[PDB]
Length: 49
Image 1: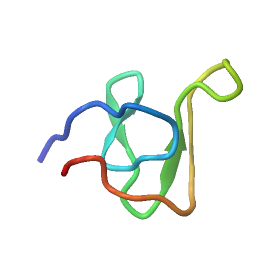
Image 2: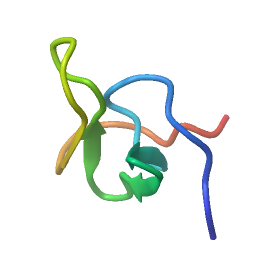
Image 3: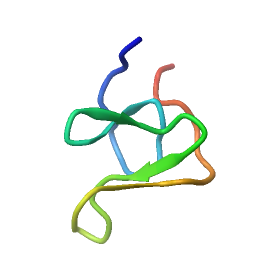
C-alpha cells in the first residue's frame, strides 16, 4: 500500500515527508515559500491519475 512521489505542495497520496506518505484525509505542503516540506491537514486531492 505505497504510493509515488508528489510533484508540488498540496497533493495527498504522495511522498512529502522525506519518503513517507503524506496526505489521505490530510494535505502536505512540500517546500513552502521556497522552503521546507511539512504535513498538515486540509483540502487537496490524490496525486495518482
